[PDB]
Image 1: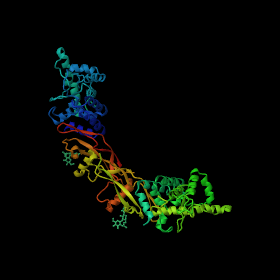
Image 2: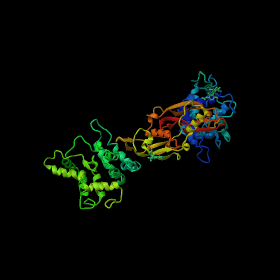
Image 3: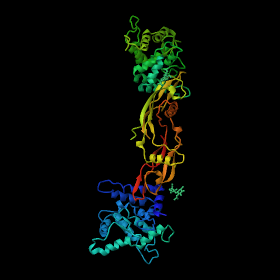
Image 4: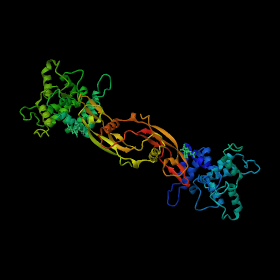
Length: 209
Length: 209
Length: 98
Length: 98
Ligand SMILES: *[C@@H]1O[C@H](CO)[C@@H](O[C@@H]2O[C@H](CO)[C@@H](O)[C@H](O)[C@H]2NC(C)=O)[C@H](O)[C@H]1NC(C)=O
Ligand SMILES: *[C@@H]1O[C@H](CO)[C@@H](O[C@@H]2O[C@H](CO)[C@@H](O)[C@H](O)[C@H]2NC(C)=O)[C@H](O)[C@H]1NC(C)=O
């Protein structure tokens, strides 16, 4: 079955999830000027409201739905469309990730949410969970907390599960290693990968639920 | 044709007359206690409102409609029912007319309206009109002005046109002549009779319209 | 918009109402009539499609109606037995798509 | 009183709405249904009698309708072409005799 489609059905059949899902799809798809497809501010704000007010079983059910193929499938494209990336994510200019990090750290909430993500999803390859903090739920909470900030992450078009904020390491200068470490915490994080996979499984894991 | 029925039809087809006609028929037919068929106060008040706010062509058309028979006919009974006499007129106790006149003269409006009636409908048999003031409209105005006071008059069951307030001259004592003069100004008044008849005619008389 | 739902009127005898009164009095009866398809919603469209789809089994829910939102003044009349009657909320005064 | 006009619901696919969308998403459609004859007026009775009397020629004015007075929250869904759509005033939230 299409797990992402099943999660969308379950959401529209729940009064709370249906209301707040539409409450962000409308501003994230409503053009308000001839220059921008959306009001990106209101799109991020309503996205933050969705994950704050909708219980995780519905909000994580759509964000962390499992698919067999990570690209080109109907599952995976629906999952990629969860945050309405054409407004919330894709942008004309693609900043350097370290430059984006400086900008995020000047926002009190963005700085707070980014610190929680780096703390709660920290890898530890000695752990059977792959995380330093063997609590997948806290990692999934911290990661989903980034949605609606300038650090909004989304699934990349890859055969595996790989996510990243809208940035890259082009033109990093003498800080190429530091930038690559930053992105790899998103794109190649066994703790985050295990946490996302453990939720999609929908089973009683030792480090989740 | 039934002139009183035609006047009732014309009234219900006029927004102003229809509204204020129903505005007095409701309180004059609505029981509000187990002892009285109506609130007589509100019935008189709404009756006064009807003749004050409805143009005379409709209000006089019903009050002064002409019938061939003054009793037992469908015309004349409809005309007698114009003021809803079961509430506005008929009463358990029938006062002496002179006693009723003392009571009326203690009310500023009743005293004013009664003086206008005796002034404007004063007979003068030398006049070709039968009135001292050869202006039938003023007599009809002063008479209709009594409706809604303690002097509320109505058509009596007689072959002729004869009206009277709800009173008589029983137990008048040494003032029998004075009482008989009072009632005769209502019941046997050629000026008032001519004025009522002239309106019912619906023609251009020399002393009306 | 609901511009099609209008206020109409007809001159009738009171007996034409078939309410049991025996009288020769008359009245102007006013009613609301007209289409309301420009004031319909997705709800009304969905209704129309589900009736045709037979998906609502035997419920035939009402789409937007042309109805009175305000009623005319009360009317009174005297019957052949010399009794007065008063009718309330008998005639429309202003219309709307509801 | 209008106690017969109630809020009902049915679980449907979005395609069951026949609005042209191509998607596998679902929804709960809620509608108002039921009789409103205890909330009718002399106006509604007069209508019923004038239809039977043929006195209104071909106007068939509407009597009291069981209709929504408040609509549910907007619903959104993603179609097969990965485009989002939002429907407004598509489902009833509270009913009344109007
Ligand atoms: C009220 O009823 C009267 C009596 O039925 C109606 O007058 C009649 O109208 C019909 C057809 O229009 C005539 O053929 C009858 O001969 C008429 N009868 C009389 C005695 O005139 C009158 O039209 C009705 N009025 C309204 C407004 O409906
Ligand atoms: C949505 O549509 C699906 C697909 O048509 C419906 O599932 C079917 O229901 C019918 C009759 O109830 C079955 O005979 C079909 O075989 C079912 N098809 C499949 C693939 O299961 C489903 O019931 C619809 N859902 C709703 C809520 O209407």
